Length: 253
Image (cartoon, rainbow, N blue to C red; front, side, top):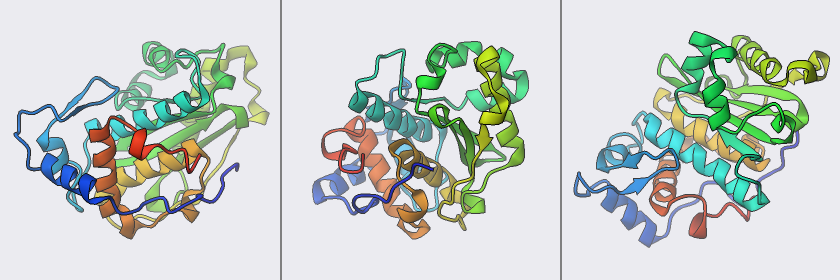
């Protein structure tokens, strides 16, 4: 499985400076560009006040994709990976709908933009694919060095859908071509904290992505009751411009 216990508490209360900064963001001038993600997406008051910070808010694409791109960038910077040879890579909210509607053969542009190519595929450690179906966010994770695919659905305490797993293996086969060895690949389920609250799916998705990207066991690392605080921490990371400085993940990597 390759997953370790977290070296310190994963979800912890913020300093007064960061709490105040997050509160100020949801009370901001509504036109201020408070942040801009690695997707190129500006974030404004609405993203924080309505689509992240309330404990019962459903997260939007801007926040979810922004956060997950920052996870991948943390790993690539830590490992000194070349820009086109990432160790962790992430997809946008457009990928899963494209895969459903076109299949992998219509996903070439999105694969290339994520730097997922045949030549470097097995050199990637973690591929993070956010999936939204019927408003419910889950996380697909391909681990090429381990030859595994996984689907982490918080509604099933981590267990994944056979339909998603099969689609992930079809994608892997498409990319790898004559390098695909079907019997050496497998779908693997990971235990993860259980979701009761529908609105928390996006927060579970981000948090499971942090854990899998870092090699941390999510079932050992957090609980659903910690997710209101995790929303504040995600907000702080976005305002900070990523998992760096105060929010480096070094002490868990």
